[PDB]
Image (cartoon, rainbow over all chains, first blue to last red; front, side):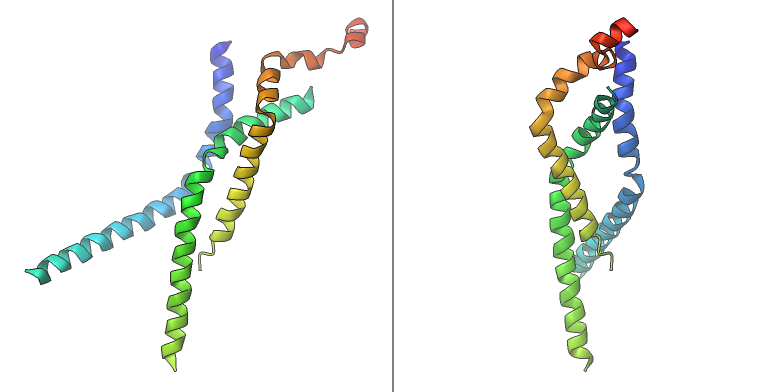
Length: 50
Length: 50
Length: 49
């Protein structure tokens, strides 16, 4: 019974958070491009400053 | 009884999504700063275009 | 032209309203959740039952 109540408590959270996947995917892509630009700028800075 | 069932259904979702306000808060701060930069870029683009 | 700031703002409105409701009725919901089943049984309806 306790496990069942815990499971049915999880189910609300489970669906609500699983709905969040796709918006987070684009956020991850954007953040990846941000990191890529960060490395590009850092590299270019290093080569010039040498 | 039915109203209580619906209330206990929504309430965990309310608790689940309440914590996201602060992560959302910084999210919109960053997003609106980005939008300010985008508006500035668009304005400056148009400014030079002529 | 993401213009998602409006969407994020709506999400904030909903989530802050949820937090406000949690503050408003958190104790009541916690006291209700362990003995919810009683609502299905109304005293006179116990006799009719």
